[PDB]
Length: 194
Length: 192
DNA sequence: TTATTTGTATCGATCACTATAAATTT
DNA sequence: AAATTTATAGTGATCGATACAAATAA
Image 1 (cartoon, rainbow over the protein chains, first blue to last red):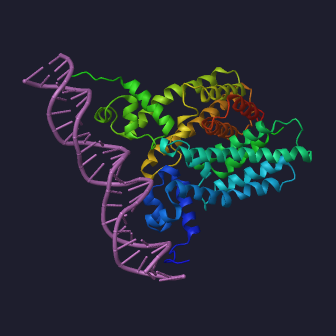
Image 2 (image 1 turned 45 degrees about the vertical axis):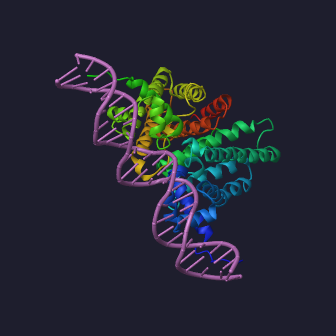
Image 3 (image 1 turned 135 degrees about the vertical axis):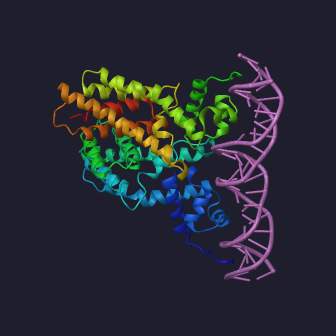
C-alpha cells in the first residue's frame, strides 16, 4: 500500500489516550492533553481516529478488552455464582486500588454528566454499565442450572444489587478509600447473598 | 442604589439544577446565565466566579437534599431502621421527577481537567461526610443497644455509603424505583 | 508519478470573564 | 446628582477540528 509509513504505533497511541480519558473523563480530556500523551499531532489523530468521539469509542473498546476480560474470566471460572461474584468483586477492588492504573472504573467515571453535546458518549457508557448487570445476571443463570442458586431467584434483582455495589466501588476508589476498607465492603455485600 | 432585577436564592436554584444535570465543567456560563435569567456581569457581581457560583449552589443543594438525611437517621429508634429509612427516602428522591435523578454530589465532578481539582476535592470531602453520617448513627446504635458493641462501624458505614453512591449511578441510568428499592432491601440483608 | 503521513499554523466557535456606560434607584 | 445594577460587547485563551505543503513511501 502506497504512502509515507505511519510514524507511531496505533495501539500505543490508543492506549495512551484511554489513560487520559480514564483520569480526566471524556469531556475533560482535551485535544492538547490527548496529543501530548499520545506523542502525535492533531491531524495524525484525526486521520487515524476520525474525531474525539471516535477516539474515545476506540479507547473504550480497548479498555473493555484489556480491563474487562478479567470480569468474565473469574466469573465463568468459579464453581458457584456466589464465589464468582465474590472473586470478581475482590479482583475489581484490587484493580481499583492498584498503583499501576488510574483508580476506579473508566466506564463509571468518564462521563456521568456533561454538556448535551456529549450525550452519545454518556449513553454509550450507560449501555456498558447495563452490560455489567447483564454479566452478573448471566453467571447467576448458570448458578441456577448448576444447582448453587435457587430456581426462583430473582436474577435481575440480585445482579442489580451487586452492580450497585460495584459502581459505588469506583467512587470510593476515586476517593482513595484504602484497599483494606473496600475488601471489607465486598465481604459485607456477600453477606446479602440469598 | 438601583434595585437588582433577580432573586439571589432563585438564581442559585437554577444554577444548581444546571450543575445537577450537566456537572461542574459541563455547565457553561452561557447555560447558567440562561437558566438564572441574569447576564454575566450580574453573575460575577453576586458569586465572584464560576467556582464560587458552584460552591454556593453546593451549599444551597446540601441545605435541601442534605439536612433531611441526619433527620431521618436520628428519627428512627434504631441504627438499622435509620439506615433503611434514609436509603428508602433517597431512592424516592432519586426517582421523583421534580429533581434530576441521582445525587449532585456524586454526579457533578468525578473526573475533569486539572483546573477543577478543587471542586472535585470538595465533592469528595462531601462524600466522606455521608460516610460520617452513617458511622455517627451507628455509634448511637451501639450506645442505645440496637447494635452490638463490637460491630465494625467503619466497614458498615462504608458499605452503605457504597450502596448510596451506586444508587446515583443507577438512578442516572433510569433504573426503575421498584428495582432500586429492592437493592435497598437487599443491602439491608447485610446488616449484622 | 500518485498516495499517505507529517508538522506548522491556523480556523471559527465557544470558554470563563470583564470594561464600560446606560438605566434605574435615592 | 450619587450609588448601584444592568445590558452590550467584547477580552485573550482554549476548544475541537482542519488547510496546506514538505516528507516519504509505492
